[PDB]
Length: 255
Length: 255
Image (tube, rainbow over all chains, first blue to last red):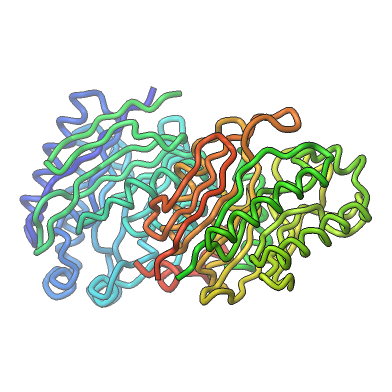
């Protein structure tokens, strides 16, 4: 009895008015289709431009974007997952993901642990906390961001805390078909969970993003998927015990 | 410049003379084809019959099988990976894998850490040591057994110790297509390694084994694969930095 939506679109670098207008439109359309939650892509509000976020995006501008996003969840009556720079100064913040419910209450916040490449590592501070897991809509939801999901340890950390549905804002460019095609199905199977992966698409900030937004069920099967063009993917989620069998006390000594 | 072979066949429960004759034949044929190493399936010497191994297979019988296997590696001039019950009494041994070189020297021994199901757990003691990693043929080889490979932690443990080629005796039944089809490609991609997976095939000990033996390269692609019938798969191996980027000191606290 759960219907989720994923927004796949192109953001304009450094134009949160435009980018949040796009999220607002997607939230309205998702709600009209009966979706109870909308997942949006990594850093969408400011575009995926790490060095320019560090150089030009102030904490006050981030907070104004966050306030508008909270208002979108409330005013469109839909839970919303967004991803922004963190709230600290440009030199002390990371990349984050947050979930607000349909009343605008922020239920969970998370800072990306696995930063991708030298530009992200120059612009952002990595997170130090495990993914949050919380009850919403009858299930345990969790958050990860982009590159995080490519590490089995990060998805296992969520599943170990009870996660059943892992929601992943992303920004995957360069025709990296192995991430949705190979890694995501395994993350689902090896934990027995569902994952939702919402990407940018098309040229943005000097890159051409892959699209390919997808929801993968616990058998590793796509429940729905997009191609390379902007779209709003709406998916109805249906109603080996690796998590129990794993010898975690040995594994943690062997990493 | 490395050519490996995988034996896929059906074993007869409790008939090591017959089963080791089959391994001897495969070793001869692999060597004739220029393969430098033969990988064989889990518990092949006695058949995959855990409860009957515990009830009827003595330590003396295991040692005699091990001695014959060492002689096969030496006399067929090929490195050999086999899997037998461990050397202790029936009540204190596990499922093991060992690698002998073409001179019959045992280079590495390993005890399966992740036992599969109640019959294995009643018949065998789980291992407590990480997978071994060793130089052979110009590369770092490692060993895991069956269900081990389905845990990302077990393959990561090997790759963290330098493994480049992970060799996996298995006994996969019940049409479990997600293991070779979904999990194995991810284990290869997420560590940047090659994996070789040698299964039983056909009815044996009350089960019908899947076959599907496969070698998967670091892009997650099958370099060679078998179907459901007995066969000898011969594969020539060619000449994101997940292993460096992973925040292992955080991950080990989150499992």
